[PDB]
Image (cartoon, grey):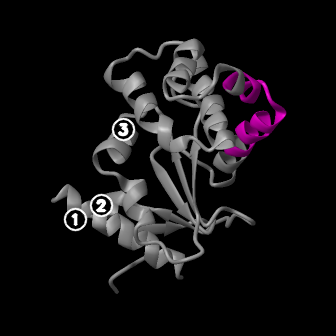
Amino acid sequence: AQYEDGKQYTTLEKPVAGAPQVLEFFSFFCPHCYQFEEVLHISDNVKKKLPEGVKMTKYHVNFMGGDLGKDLTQAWAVAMALGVEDKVTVPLFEGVQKTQTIRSASDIRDVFINAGIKGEEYDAAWNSFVVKSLVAQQEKAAADVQLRGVPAMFVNGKYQLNPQGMDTSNMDVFVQQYADTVKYLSEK
């Protein structure tokens, strides 16, 4: 058939109860994640085709970058808590990977301050238990899908996107196939 298990997607041996409908994992340290987000715009292209009533969730991971990687997971929790993901995603990626001006937790905070988030507001969120629970949620979700690497995307806690079974061709044909595959899985 057109879409096949083992080709555009794989199936989790162990389905995740109560998982987000569309769940993406990434790291701001991850070079392919930079490509996915800043060049391919995978997240955005996926959203443009999702059925009505289907939400996308995106989580950061700890396993790249040591202490800073964990700082970035905590900052991503802050971004989610404050609802400013679309203000900090580009400057965090560029700060870590393009300019390499993000080397500490303070440098991360600077991105938020420069994006217009008040210092008090960031610090309050950073130290909050709501953010601690959001960090834990991200770590638990990684465990639940038995995550090995990023970028990664899972649909209804049952299916894993398999980009290596798509074409690399026109980056654009790749992106279209990826987005179309998520939509197909959403309706499965």
Instruction: Say which quadrant the N terminus sits in.
Output: bottom left
Please name the residue that numbered disc 3 is placed on: 34
Of the numbered discs 1 and 3, the one sitting upstream in the chain is: 3
Q: Residue at x 48, y 13 (%)?
A: 103
Q: CA distance from mark 2 to mark 3?
A: 14 Å
Q: What amino acid is labelled 2 in the image?
A: Val
Query: Magenta stretch mostly in which secondary structure?
Result: helix
Answer yes or no: do the residues labelled 1 and 2 have beta carbons within 8 Å?
A: yes
Q: Which mark is residue 175?
A: 2
Which contiguous range is marked in magenta?
122-138
Q: Position of residue 166 (x, y in %)?
A: 29, 64
Q: Quadrant of residue 99?
A: top left
Residue 29 visible in the current orientation: no
Q: Position of residue 182 (x, y in %)?
A: 45, 69
Q: What amino acid is labelled 3 in the image?
A: Tyr
Q: Position of residue 140 (x, y in %)?
A: 72, 46
